[PDB]
Image: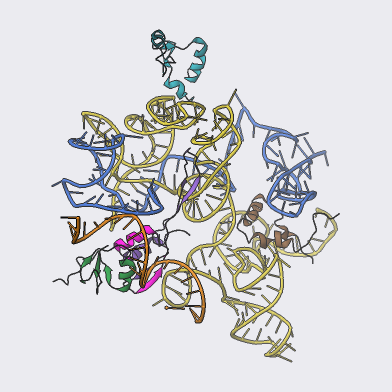
Chain colours: A cyan, B brown, C green, D purple, E orange, F blue, G yellow
Amino acid sequence: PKMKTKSSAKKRFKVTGSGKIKRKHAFKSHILTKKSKKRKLALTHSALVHKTDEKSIKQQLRII
Amino acid sequence: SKRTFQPSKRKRRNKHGFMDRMASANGRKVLARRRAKGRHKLTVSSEPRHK
Amino acid sequence: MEIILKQDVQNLGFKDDVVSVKPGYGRNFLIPQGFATLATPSAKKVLAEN
Amino acid sequence: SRVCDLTGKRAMVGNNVSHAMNKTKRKFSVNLVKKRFYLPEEDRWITLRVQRSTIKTINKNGITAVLKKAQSAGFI
RNA sequence: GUUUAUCUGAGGCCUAACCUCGCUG
RNA sequence: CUGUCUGAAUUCGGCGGGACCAUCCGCUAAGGCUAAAUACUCCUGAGAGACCGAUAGUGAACCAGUACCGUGAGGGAAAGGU
RNA sequence: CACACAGAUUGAUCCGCAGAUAUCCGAAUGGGGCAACCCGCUAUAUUGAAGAUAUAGCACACCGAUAGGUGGGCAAACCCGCUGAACUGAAACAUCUAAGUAGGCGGAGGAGAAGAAAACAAAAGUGAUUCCGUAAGUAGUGGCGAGCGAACGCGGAUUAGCCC
């Protein structure tokens, strides 16, 4: 029947304006006191899903 | 040697007879299944007696 | 409960008076022995006080 | 069976959820008691298998009213 | 510090729910 | 909705609007009945197939749930044409 | 079919509908029993009397006060209620899924269930239930894993409301 969208992928992975997928960064959860402020500032802005994972992310989001 | 089937035309009827199938509630479903399938021979009581 | 005594009770007494007892004292003793009647639809039916 | 005579209250089926959410079938039984009720309007004794919950409504209303209400609906 | 009407913790006693036995209630 | 226990008021009352409270809005529980549009084929009458044509099509086109196997539940064939 | 024997324009044979008879076992119902069997009681008649016969009535539960009525059991699927798994998936597995599925039990009808607001909605409004298409794989739910997944509103089929 209708293809179901994976919830784990739909709660993350916001689709951008034209053809990209926007996601968040990791490692910024609970040990932030010993990481440099440079890493914590770089891991704050949103990132894009790489082209090697784009096919899998699109198959999960039901955009073949 | 002694085989497994030692016939007895009363031990047969006391175990597989019509009145033994009709006495139980679940033994009465065997009759229904056989009549639905269309068995020409029902329980062993259908075998003719000696005349 | 709410019983209406009929003859007498040692600690209750004063028949024709609404008394509150524990459920199990009027049901097992007073009702079977005729000392009280469980009378909920009788507060108005008791007109002998007139 | 194990049902009340004046209400027809049957048992219930449910689960036995443990601490780790393990579920197992379980039967909530009725608190049936075998009392011996005295009829005040007829001076007679009957033996029923009523529940402790309908004993309460008997003490609330009266044995005669409860019996006349249970007579309807076929003792249920 | 005691008294009066309730709650509760324990014992004793009574029979009237409940259980059991003997003659047939 | 309740297996157990407890337990309310009667219309300036009661319930709901996704914890809960105040204001607004809606409804009036603890009684009952009710056709149509909806699902199926042990069957019945009529009629079709870019459906099979005897190792195919129902297990069974033919003395088929038959012959055979088992104590029993039960399993289960082959076999059309001058 | 064959050797035959008969019936039939006085109208046969045949078809449609409506009737009669309908042995025994089987719910089996007079008792029993190893289904197709055995053995009875009360009324009548037959040698009537022993051995036996012919006809009728003899099970159970309910209600009807009484002459008597109702139900036993079987059988496709749909529907309702009470119970109710595991394999499998999670690339292991216990929460979860499989699934309220398979299976078991009881009842009714051509359908059944539901059905007339202690309802939705939101500052604008609709007005019983059922079914079809969207809403929507959305909101949400989930060892937030596998997975599960509405509702509001809109368009249609039908339309009916009443009794304590």
> In the displayed image of the protein, which residue is found farthest to the top?
A38
Q: Is residue A1 above or below residue D48?
A: above
- Which residues make up the magenta segment? D43-62
> Depth check: G49 or B20 in front?
B20
Marks counted in the figure total 0
Q: Position of residue C18 (x, y in %)?
A: 21, 66
> In the displayed image of the protein, which residue is found farthest to the left?
C50
Q: Is residue D23 visible?
A: yes
Q: Is residue F82 above or below residue D60?
A: above
Q: Is residue G52 above or below residue G3?
A: below
Q: Position of residue D17 (x, y in %)?
A: 47, 42
Residue at image coords 34%, 74%? D43
Residue at image coords 33%, 71%? C32
Is residue G146 shown left or right of residue F70?
A: left
Q: Is residue A64 visible?
A: no
Q: Position of residue G54 (x, y in %)?
A: 66, 78
Is residue G42 shown left or right of residue A2?
A: right
> Depth check: F44 or D46 in front?
D46
> Depth check: F36 or F70 in front?
F70
Q: Is residue F13 above or below residue E25?
A: above
Q: Position of residue F77 (x, y in %)?
A: 76, 42
Residue at image coords 32%, 70%? C29
Is residue G127 shown left or right of residue G94?
A: left
> Depth check: C14 or D45 in front?
C14
Magenta run includes residue B15 = no
Residue at image coords 74%, 62%? B11
Magenta run includes residue D59 = yes
